[PDB]
Image (cartoon, rainbow over all chains, first blue to last red; front, side):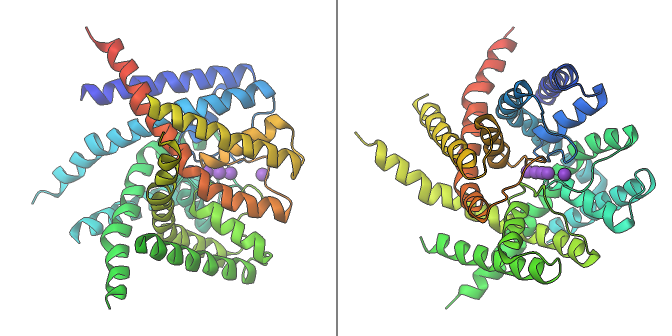
Length: 93
Length: 93
Length: 93
Length: 93
Ligand SMILES: [K+]
Ligand SMILES: [K+]
Ligand SMILES: [K+]
Ligand SMILES: [K+]
Ligand SMILES: [K+]
């Protein structure tokens, strides 16, 4: 419980940072910077944008190595400690 | 057995939702909306399309966090509890 | 040992199938069809091509669910049962 | 500790190799070759570039199978043995 809360806050902050950077350095709209941050950390990849500035490319490299771990951690616990029980409870005859 | 069935149905529903949304909000053909939903949740990424509407971008963000977990769960059990035995049985001298 | 060999052959066959399909249905060169098959199953994603035919889009969907599992299995054992020992042996004072 | 150091050096070398290849064979700038190497091994995918030469496509295929394992290994230990403790220490009442 408190674990998922911590991972949630950590993820929120990680995304906020991405939103602020890509909207300031790469000139994206707040919503687009968020989207790029999300698809990047989850490794989906954005097909409509790639960092154009060397500053953006360097940041993304570091942003990736530092973000993917905690992002998938959240996704992990989000599924295991939240998504799993809900479906099991719905099954119970 | 019953586990893979549950994960299969859950995945089917998850994809159906994606197909309906992207074909209604993003104006994709049913088959293309399905494809985008699949390549997104499996993190492959679609190189020929990205949500153009802010509504589409927001949904995708949430769709990703909620879908990736169960999708890879299915892929996991699909491989372990289905793909693995089949190949082992084929090996048996 | 024999495990990595099995996973290797399985992966080879999986890629061969992809190479033959994408070069026949999507009209790609043999090398490009292979590349697309590789970047898709490893979830990297191809930024220069997406299936144009409905036949190609349907196949890719199934190809993804069936391929990712064994591909990452190979990558897993390739790293653990092959890449890991080699680096450890190189460390030994 | 010494484990993360080994995985770090291994990753650095893996990326250096990618940077040198893509800047020599694919004619990318050093920073862009590095970026492509990073987004590829982490499976994010690059939406602004794909190998144009058959030499580049073949190398990438092998580069992927050999790199993803150690890259995610680093990301794994980077998160578990470095990122995890730091956040836990920050929590302690
Ligand atoms: K990707
Ligand atoms: K892509
Ligand atoms: K991926
Ligand atoms: K991608
Ligand atoms: K493109």
